[PDB]
Length: 432
Ligand SMILES: O=C1N[C@@H]2[C@@H](O)[C@@H](O)[C@H](O)[C@@H](CO)N2C1=O
Ligand SMILES: [Ca+2]
Ligand SMILES: [Ca+2]
Ligand code: NA
Image (cartoon, rainbow, N blue to C red; front, side, top):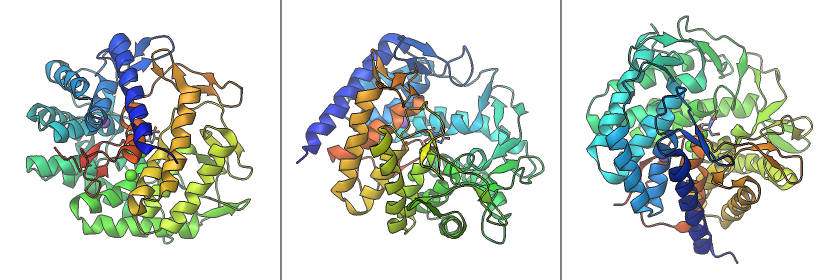
């Protein structure tokens, strides 16, 4: 039988080794390219904001990598400024930087990390204020407030309430919670008679710009943040809306192909199937199904992705649901499978979820390890699988934390109170 504590130690060792590569090759920069041993920018070309450092902080603290955590916190306090004449994508900036500063604040108690999270949220608020509906524009200039691109989508208007609602709790100012909730209510009030929303929306007209309902591309984390706002804030509207939206998806989007459960895109009014693609991103939804009281359905959905892992090694970035085969050969070093394994495991503690996640971690080690860290893949169909040259910022917050939480039973987390954002930032449950 597997020694889960020895596996947790191995995860921690690999994470510390990756951190050392970041310090050596990419210190203060947004992402490491771990094959070349170089860095790249994420938000603003040539004006890095320490993205991967910020994304790593709560993971380092949970693992007891205290010297490394403090080195990162001290860098942020000396160096990280948002008074920058450049355009930032509102969605990415909130889930990665506001959320990463909040989880590091909650772990450490350090007021400067909260001050920086709040400064950044106030710059992002200008994107919501530029719409008469309160729907955020996709980009905002961090210094001047000027906005660009109102042709947005459910994920990019509806993935704010966890971070903004925690800011409201800590600061006492309800304006953040209210701004985030108003944008979600807009699209919920425009549900069709069958209970679905199209995934594409215009921030100035307030109207849908497509007819496609989705659980993945353009939409994923909207549905997650409805449940999460009930769990974090006790919001009764969000509890109702979470269950309503998922029951509409199970009635009109759930379809079986070759005996396996999938959720293709459909016309939001008629329910006709409008696409045959499913993203790897959709695997999050197996865990959301369990959280909202649909665990049998969640397990059935997880099984579709378990099939893909057993057949292809690495889950394909996109599949055709009619054949079960890849639509793309590259990957993004994606975290959604161990996300779902952790969320289902928190319900019943079944060791099956540990065995499935251990396969996923061992496959990551066999395919993505490079000279100075872990990289996304070029082609999952060759042997060996060929590599690209990038460690995405979300790797530092997500799958190494998921594996460690599944295997370590760490005393630094109250597992009964644990709450994670869509970027895996811990927003409740630290034990100091
Ligand atoms: O479209 C995306 N959705 C998810 C996000 O919810 C978050 O998990 C990561 O930024 C990242 C992990 O794959 N994601 C995306 O690129
Ligand atoms: Ca996510
Ligand atoms: Ca979640
Ligand atoms: Na983080």
